[PDB]
Length: 64
Length: 64
Image 1: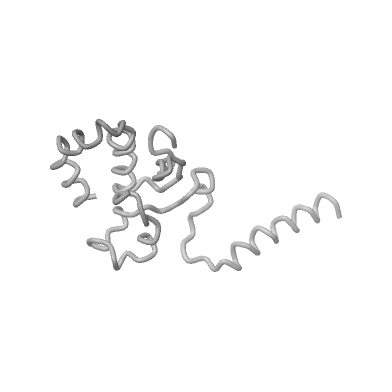
Image 2 (image 1 turned 45 degrees about the vertical axis):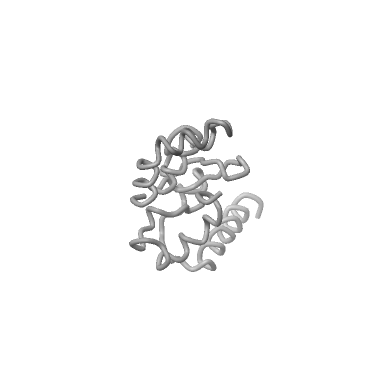
C-alpha cells in the first residue's frame, strides 16, 4: 500500500519529486500507441485535425 | 510488455493485481521487480522476506 498508493500525479509535478528526477516516476503509455508519440508540444488541435483531415483526404479519394 | 521492457514500456500489477502499461523508468523497473519477488509472496512469508531484504529495499527506494 505505501509503495503503490497515489502513484500517478508525480509525472505531472516533477518539482515535488526527489532530484526532480522523471526516472523515479510512473508515466502511463501504450506500447503500440508509442510508435506515433514523437513530436513534443504539438498543439492538440494540430494532432486531432491531422487525424480527421487524413480521414477526409483518403475518403475523398476512394468514394468521391 | 508482460515479461521485459518492449519499446520502452512495461506491464506492472496495481495494488488490486490489475495490469498497467507504464514507460519502463528506473522507478517502474523497481515496481516490476518488487511485483516478481516481494508482493507475490503469501502473507506468512511477507514480513520475514522484508526484514531479510530491508537494506536492499531501502537503497533502491532512495536511489530509484
